[PDB]
Amino acid sequence: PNHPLWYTLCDRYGLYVVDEANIETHGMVPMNRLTDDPRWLPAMSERVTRMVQRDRNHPSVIIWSLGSESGHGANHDALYRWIKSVDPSRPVQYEGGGADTTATDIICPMYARVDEDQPFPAVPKWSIKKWLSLPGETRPLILCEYAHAMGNSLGGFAKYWQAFRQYPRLQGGFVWDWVDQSLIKYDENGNPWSAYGGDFGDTPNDRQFCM
Amino acid sequence: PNHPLWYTLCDRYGLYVVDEANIETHGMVPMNRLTDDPRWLPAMSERVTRMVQRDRNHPSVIIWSLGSESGHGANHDALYRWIKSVDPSRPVQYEGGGADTTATDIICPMYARVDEDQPFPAVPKWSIKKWLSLPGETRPLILCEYAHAMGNSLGGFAKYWQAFRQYPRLQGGFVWDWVDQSLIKYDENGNPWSAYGGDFGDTPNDRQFCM
Ligand SMILES: CC(C)S[C@@H]1O[C@H](CO)[C@H](O)[C@H](O)[C@H]1O
Ligand SMILES: CC(C)S[C@@H]1O[C@H](CO)[C@H](O)[C@H](O)[C@H]1O
Ligand code: NA
Ligand code: NA
Ligand code: NA
Ligand code: NA
Image (cartoon, rainbow over all chains, first blue to last red):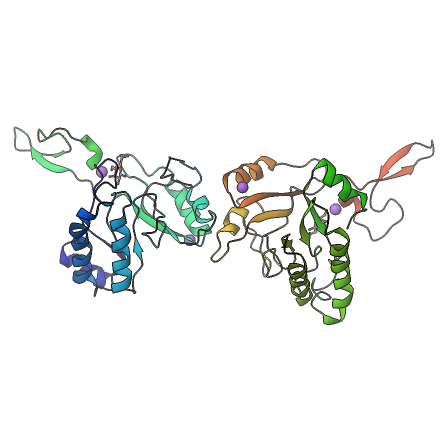
């Protein structure tokens, strides 16, 4: 959840917002180790429920999200249903555990390609055009993350937009991402320069992946 | 419906058969002028019912078809339901009136392209990949006709097969068609040659389109 003024400005200027719970357990092995564990359900529930209690009156918020990159656990299903029960007015989405689990109203993959399948075991990233028409599938597809804009990038961005415009159920996506996470440091002359992972003696680090 | 021996050979050699009622009204304006008219229901019904009564025991027949290129009329709906009621063991398909009407279990377009939409009014031919995932659509797609093999043709055939293999619900199609409808005529030297529309003084004719 963002600084409270963010939603005020989104209401007044006009942006659709996905409001997302402060839950990410990416570094767990497997990714759902905590989110499938009932012991972690109370802590998780508060991150979801207190977000909804705070932001439910903002018109800019059109979708709730259960968080980011935490696999798919039973705790996700429980909290998905909590929101659906408490606030029928907004769909709930969540990408973890394959982007099309029982905890999401929207197929919301990250970095699924337009035409190319990536058939990873358990959590494949189907071509977005193919994903829509899989046997039994009926949901809309909106990438929670696509077009990783890291450095000299956004090659093949036009390919997404062509597909979005042609297929009714391909309803767009959220680019990753808005702003480089570089920090200002100062050299011997007091001149400012942009720094990234590792430039603060921080180790282990992931270098320029913050940009 | 074919010569009776055809089904016997398909049973024994092993080919899947679509058995099709002898109903085509292509030259009507509009195409459903007769098929939507209750006066023509009796004649149409016998073309359907007597086919089913003849061929229902052949294992090679897996799909019934209501005919060809006769638009979509209420008579098709009636006869669709008739077959479904009499023989639940085989799907019913029919392409007329846009290939995805209430008279078909299978989306069965003719010459719909792989990636290219052709948004004709009333009867659009969507790209087959796009067709599958139109809002609400759940049926399999098998082209009743595709890859028109007229003369030097089958350009782009590989594009179809790549899509068939990638998308579970694209379950193939029937090439148009098997054999040139050329006829033998004889010249002065008694030599046989291959003749097409117009070569018998037949007029109006559609020239080489029989091949
Ligand atoms: C396969 C890994 C690089 S995960 C990848 O890292 C990205 C780095 O910018 C983002 O954080 C994405 O959300 C994450 O999926
Ligand atoms: C627009 C017309 C060419 S219709 C077209 O003609 C073809 C010619 O072989 C086939 O008969 C197809 O079934 C028919 O749709
Ligand atoms: Na769209
Ligand atoms: Na990053
Ligand atoms: Na297929
Ligand atoms: Na022809």
